[PDB]
Amino acid sequence: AATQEEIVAGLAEIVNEIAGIPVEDVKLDKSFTDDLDVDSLSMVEVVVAAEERFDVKIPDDDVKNLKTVGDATKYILDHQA
Image 1 (cartoon, helix red, strand yellow):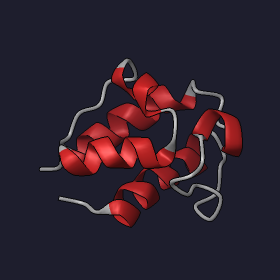
Image 2 (tube, helix red, strand yellow):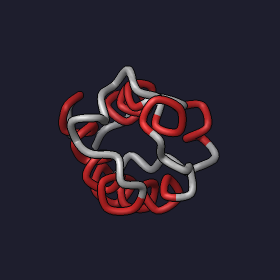
Image 3 (cartoon, helix red, strand yellow):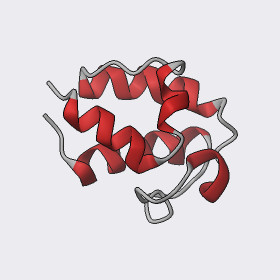
Image 4 (cartoon, helix red, strand yellow):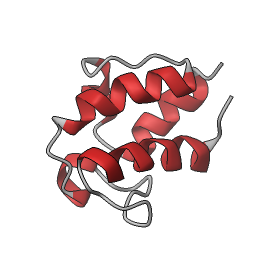
């Protein structure tokens, strides 16, 4: 069970790798594909990476409803394992 910043940093590190949004930039108020820059395509791989680390499992489909780091974090934290 991760927490707000753990989900954030976790998503962020993956983002840093594929999309290129740095961990400082990825904050919960940040819409990955709007605030940050994330091409949303990276998000697909951020998903399988996040799902695997969080065990929460948020398909990119449900990820659409999580159009912000904090929204994702909200979902991911509430659904943590």
